[PDB]
Amino acid sequence: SSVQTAATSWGTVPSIRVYTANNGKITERCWDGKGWYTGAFNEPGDNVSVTSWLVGSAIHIRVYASTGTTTTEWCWDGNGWTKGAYTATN
Amino acid sequence: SSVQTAATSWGTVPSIRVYTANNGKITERCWDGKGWYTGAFNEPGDNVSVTSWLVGSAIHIRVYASTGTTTTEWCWDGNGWTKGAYTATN
Amino acid sequence: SSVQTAATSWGTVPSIRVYTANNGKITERCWDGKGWYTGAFNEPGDNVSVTSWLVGSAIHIRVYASTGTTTTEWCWDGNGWTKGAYTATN
Ligand SMILES: OC[C@@]1(O)OC[C@@H](O)[C@@H](O)[C@@H]1O
Ligand SMILES: OC[C@@]1(O)OC[C@@H](O)[C@@H](O)[C@@H]1O
Ligand SMILES: OC[C@@]1(O)OC[C@@H](O)[C@@H](O)[C@@H]1O
Ligand SMILES: OC[C@@]1(O)OC[C@@H](O)[C@@H](O)[C@@H]1O
Ligand SMILES: OC[C@@]1(O)OC[C@@H](O)[C@@H](O)[C@@H]1O
Ligand SMILES: OC[C@@]1(O)OC[C@@H](O)[C@@H](O)[C@@H]1O
């Protein structure tokens, strides 16, 4: 009966992203060094995980949002969220 | 009815931290290359996530502990755990 | 009643590993830059977390699989999964 979170970070300041699954919806809070704010990610899901990697100074984020046995991958690559190629046969 | 864990690591040896939420309490186990031991983190929460980053050789850890819809951020920056500025309106 | 995932990544292409706990079993999907495929990890568990680190170009993965209050660590160090030394007194 609690929310469920996932977190990732990059750099040294750092930048942080925290995803919260709450009543079937996943939202995103962001830190870039000067206060928390609400990010552009808002998608359905009961469970969330995240990973990210830098290429130079460019961040790439992958969020795995699951409802039932269906996991949807969401991708941030500098210019908006897009649905990723991830599949699994759960 | 199972415990729930979160893990982070840094360096090459490496150092590892594993957080376990169990019956509303989050505790920490630590690896620095020569055996597992119990860490200083002990806080209430039904759900845990973690991220960390290095600045040179200095580790910074953020633990997100949630009870109900309330997420509390805990910060390690070399000299003790402190409550962080994270908020969310869940 | 949803599956539960954990994710890690390394490099710049990148490589990604996504672990899914589903009905007491944890399986692994892999991305190395040219399509998702099923990995060698298949172990019992209701809950999963993961962390990984590079040593040069060599990846090291630690997966924490929990059933009830018992967490088992699984280790990938380039040549097969092995059970790790992790213990906790949950
Ligand atoms: O600057 C904030 C932002 O653009 O950062 C990258 C992603 O986390 C986005 O969802 C988010 O809105
Ligand atoms: O679209 C970006 C993408 O190719 O990045 C690597 C993996 O995350 C893929 O599933 C994903 O589709
Ligand atoms: O050396 C152990 C320790 O100081 O490492 C940093 C943090 O994980 C602390 O909670 C922990 O007690
Ligand atoms: O106190 C340390 C701090 O500033 O570090 C960056 C973010 O984790 C903040 O929420 C946090 O308060
Ligand atoms: O190339 C795939 C593979 O060998 O990568 C490392 C680990 O993720 C293994 O479980 C997996 O089968
Ligand atoms: O076997 C590899 C190992 O030594 O790596 C570091 C830690 O993950 C240990 O628990 C583990 O046993």
Image: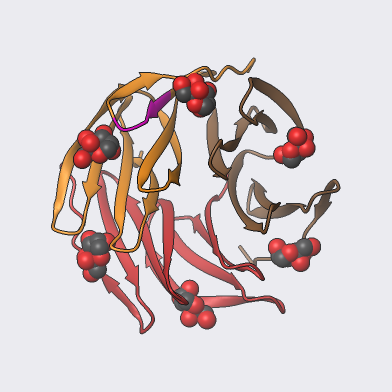
Chain colours: A red, B brown, C orange
Q: Is residue C67 visible?
A: no
Q: In which quarter of the image is the C terminus of chain C?
A: top right
| Residue B25 vs residue C16, the one in the foreground | C16
The picture places residue C13, in percent across and down from the top left corner, at 28, 63
Expressed as whole percent of the image width and height from the top left, the position of residue C32 reads 22, 53
In terms of depth relative to the viewer, which is nearer, B26 or B11?
B11
Assign ligand 4 to one image quadrant.
bottom right
Image quadrant assignment for residue C62: top left
Q: In which quarter of the image is the N terminus of chain C?
A: top left
Compared to residue A60, the image places residue C75 above or below, namely above
Residue interval drawn in magenta = C74-78
**Which residue is found at the position 36% from the left and 42% from the top?**
C58
Residue at x 34%, y 63% (from the top left corner): C12
Seen in the image, is B40 located left or right of residue A41? right
The percent position of residue C77, horizontal first and vertical second, equals 36, 31
In the image, A66 versus C70, the foreground residue is: C70
**A26 inside magenta stretch:** no
Please give left or right for residue C10 compared with residue B57 in the image: left
Q: Main secondary structure of the magenta part?
A: strand
